[PDB]
């Protein structure tokens, strides 16, 4: 079973959008969101990846309690939120904590309730609504196999460097 | 200058939607929102009102720091968010704290930045997006005079009882 | 399907043990726990009940986000934690929010993961460990039917008054 | 040993100054402080008192963890902060939780460290510095006996009504 | 228009005074303040500066929501709080987030309300009141031009190294 | 008087167990505890130590207000919690902030109230109760001298490397 380290940038419940400078590893405030919205899960990126858009591959991690920005979480994928924004491809791997038996019933995208998946989708569809020249189109859920392959190829691209 | 007491039900930043039972005065959890959204201001209702829809008149209060549910705040109106939902009329009076000189520059709807007003509007336009058979249409900002008249007539309707 | 109002006294995560004075309805700090423990769910009591011990019947409510003390939550039972302490019978009805489709898959005690139920049990087994002359014995989970009957008879006892 | 109920209005760490309407028992936001200061202890008033200034007698309660506004705490006095402000006499009884053995070593004003007492004094000396026509003079610590007598006489004044 | 990176050490609302070790970049707890006061804005220092006192130049950043210690914020100056303490010169650049149109109306020190500026001043005037052998004198607000020049010369001093 | 730097991993009140990767210095989420328990003090490790078990020496730091994970605190020891777990020796040095006169009355293990020491012990005795193949035996408090010697020898072991 695949697993990897996610650096969490943004705790669940946050309207401050934090990024990491990937040169330094410093956490940065990107912006306070222009919409009255809050990240619906802990959000970050997979360490040692180069995604389909030239940045590290983004990840959403389901947690019982949020963490702080910059914290590492060992995670395994169960699906992916596929999307294109003004930046091009901007896919998000849905994960759960690896090696934690309390998540053993969550193996694939169909094991995550529709209410959670719709909520996550709603966030990404709408959070940029009041920023002009920023859209999102092609927004879909895909299964674990598709998530694994995208992580796989983004690990290879990182190594080719 | 008009002023009144607002009972705050929902602090700013909250995804739990609290109501008051107006028979008892008890605070109740209505629901946890189905959208990844958070109340953009402290939200409640004006005491001793009967609004255009038969409930107390709703109010949004701009505060430097949120309060707890059930707290009274003496407030004065500066504008109103006019809207119709599945319940019919569901207008919200925009207020600031009364008798507080730090808010003396905020007198009318044009004294509130567009970014705040758009954010508030976005909340009310979208927070019910994942609840079926719940829409909102006719969503507009109106000035202080219109707010005063609606409070005025809702105070009179309460007294006629 | 049975439902009722729970007044939440103690949010999940709390080490302050709050009670309600049932004469007045005032919230009171009973004590700060003597153990390094925290209420594992939102905790309160069912309004209009007289339990098997002469106090209102206690309830645990599973919520996506905790509420504040004194808030009402409409809830339905899915099981019960049966126990006897130094006070005699001190049973706790396990509930979920009523009329909320996100909880429709949780119908009976077997629909709640063992890790949650063990955690709840551990709290009640151990939280009084450093208070002398306070024990708990006979600690067991029972199903929804048993919970319904105990609520039923505690509603009747309240009415006979 | 004397004890009484304190209704806490303001948790420790707060810059929102909450009051209770003593007619209704409703919690109200008085104001957000004009100084960058925060209440150094949980702050409220003793129920069923009429102090030397015609309001209920104010109390400071030392707690391991703050409570919410409107919560009752059974407390016993260990000293008093004597002061006169623009309102005249505005004394504050220093208390600890009653019937709690973890506070048994705190019996009188000399059992409270000077750093706490200086901090409390500093708050009350300075929190109104940026509100014009509001001063405080005559600010002193006095012992438990003086605190008891002031509670005593304020209970009698309440009863004479 | 000038801009720079501020490393925030202390979120707004905090009574823990955090510093950065500039050798390592580690965040350190300097002390819990001896006064019942709380940092009135997010507080840190400008990266790649050597101020008039041989430490990095301090900055206050006005934010809609505080950040965590160690977070970078791209900021632009609008004024400066000029002061001398027991350490000699200890000036603080007042900033707002750079490239954020919600702050475009805040260009110079006169665009910041007097109530904020007085509050900030009150903090720095009083927070060391209960630490002996620590004073502050010469405390004044100066405009953006003066702030720019001090940043300018502190950047040059850093480069000469 | 001995002092040292503690890197705090876990703030007081936390049910998320954070660790540091000692290779990188990155903070990691180890796990969310399986018990309804919360760290009773701020918890971390002494920098530049190699304890009796081959990891850095663990420390508990008594603070007036918790810090964030990864923050350094200069501390001095007053005692130690001696224990063996499934990992072998897993001792914890009890500390207070160094160079802070508010802690000058806390010099040795007998200056810490029994209620705190029992609470800390209860945490470590019970927090792994629902993780199988994880026990703790031999759990005792020892005085400052014993703490100093263990730090001493763990500093020497770090240097021999
Ligand atoms: C009652 N029911 C079906 C329930 N399932 C879960 C659960 C199943 C698989 C993972 N989780 C999980 C979700 C969120 C946090 C932690 C674990 N969690 C709960 N909780 C009240 C925490 N309830
Ligand atoms: C820098 N500038 C134009 C600014 N204006 C205000 C302000 C003007 C009128 C009311 N408020 C207000 C808004 C929110 C909270 C409190 C007061 N507040 C700030 N703050 C940083 C608090 N900055
Ligand atoms: C991934 N999985 C099985 C999951 N199930 C639930 C869930 C099922 C039934 C009720 N709940 C529930 C539990 C706690 C809070 C809200 C709802 N919730 C989650 N969350 C991450 C919130 N995950
Ligand atoms: C280490 N020492 C002398 C200490 N004393 C107390 C204490 C003595 C009497 C009352 N308290 C008390 C103070 C605040 C909260 C709770 C209890 N508390 C602590 N704590 C770390 C909580 N330490
Ligand atoms: C109603 N009035 C004059 C107002 N102005 C501002 C504002 C103007 C320029 C900057 N800010 C600002 C201040 C603090 C946070 C964010 C933005 N902000 C508010 N808020 C209620 C947030 N109100
Ligand atoms: C009333 N009494 C005996 C008391 N002692 C202390 C105290 C003595 C030595 C250290 N601490 C200390 C403990 C926890 C936090 C900060 C300092 N602290 C308090 N507080 C209410 C903070 N009370
Ligand atoms: Ca990013
Ligand atoms: Ca970006
Ligand atoms: Ca857009
Ligand atoms: Ca309502
Ligand atoms: Ca409703
Ligand atoms: Ca809808
Ligand atoms: Ca109870
Ligand atoms: Ca009790
Ligand atoms: Ca016991
Ligand atoms: Ca008062
Ligand atoms: Ca008043
Ligand atoms: Ca004054
Ligand atoms: Ca500094
Ligand atoms: Ca310093
Ligand atoms: Ca001084
Ligand atoms: Ca560790
Ligand atoms: Ca480990
Ligand atoms: Ca075990």
Image (cartoon, coloured by chain):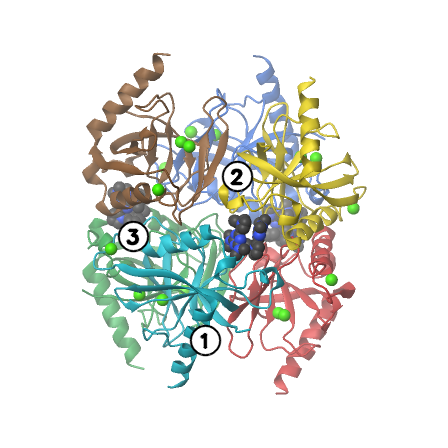
Chain colours: A blue, B green, C red, D cyan, E brown, F yellow
| Res F68 label | 2
Residue E1, given in percent of the width and then of the height, sits at 24, 25
In the structure shown, which secondary structural element does the residue marked by tag 3 occupy?
Answer: loop
In the structure shown, which secondary structural element does the residue marked by tag 1 occupy?
Answer: loop
Provide the chain ID for the residue under circle 3. Answer: D
Give the answer, above or below, for where A113 lies relative to A31.
below
Q: Which label lies toward us, 1 or 3?
A: 3
In the structure shown, which secondary structural element does the residue marked by tag 2 occupy?
Answer: loop
Q: Quadrant of the N terminus of chain D?
A: bottom right
Provide the chain ID for the residue under circle 1. Answer: B
Q: Nearer the viewer, residue B46 or F29?
A: F29
Quarter holding ligand 21: top left
Residue bearing the label numbered 1: B24
Question: Do marks 3 and 2 both belong to one polypeptide chain?
Answer: no
Q: Nearer the viewer, residue E103 or D116?
A: D116
| Res D109 label | none
Q: Residues within 10 Å of mark 1 (few under 14, many from 20)?
A: few
Q: How many numbered circles does the render carry?
A: 3
Q: Is residue B35 left or right of residue E116?
A: right
Provide the chain ID for the residue under circle 2. Answer: F
Residue bearing the label numbered 3: D34
* Residue B66 visible in the shown view: yes
Q: Residues within 10 Å of mark 2 (few under 14, many from 20)?
A: some
Q: Is residue A152 left or right of residue F99?
A: right
Question: Do marks 1 and 3 both belong to one polypeptide chain?
Answer: no
* Residue B116 visible in the shown view: no
Residue D155, given in percent of the width and then of the height, sits at 43, 79
Residue D49, given in percent of the width and then of the height, sits at 41, 76
Residue B2, given in percent of the width and then of the height, sits at 21, 66
């Amino acid at each position: 079973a695949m697993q990897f380290d996610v650096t969490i940038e943004i705790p669940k419940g946050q309207r401050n959008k934090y990024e990491v400078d990937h040169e330094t590893g410093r956490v940065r405030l990107d912006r306070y969101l222009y919409t009255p919205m809050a990240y619906p899960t802990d959000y970050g990126f997979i360490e040692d990846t180069l995604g389909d858009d030239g940045d590290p591959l983004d990840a959403l991690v389901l947690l019982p309690q949020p963490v702080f920005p910059g914290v590492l979480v060992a995670a395994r994928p169960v699906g992916m939120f596929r999307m294109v924004d003004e930046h091009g491809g901007d896919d998000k791997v849905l994960c759960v904590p690896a090696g934690d038996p309390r998540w053993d019933h969550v193996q694939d995208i169909g094991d995550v309730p529709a209410f959670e998946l719709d909520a996550i989708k709603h966030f990404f569809v709408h959070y940029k609504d009041l920023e002009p020249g920023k859209f999102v189109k092609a927004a879909d859920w895909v299964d674990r196999a598709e998530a694994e392959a995208e992580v796989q190829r983004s690990v290879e691209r990182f190594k080719a460097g």
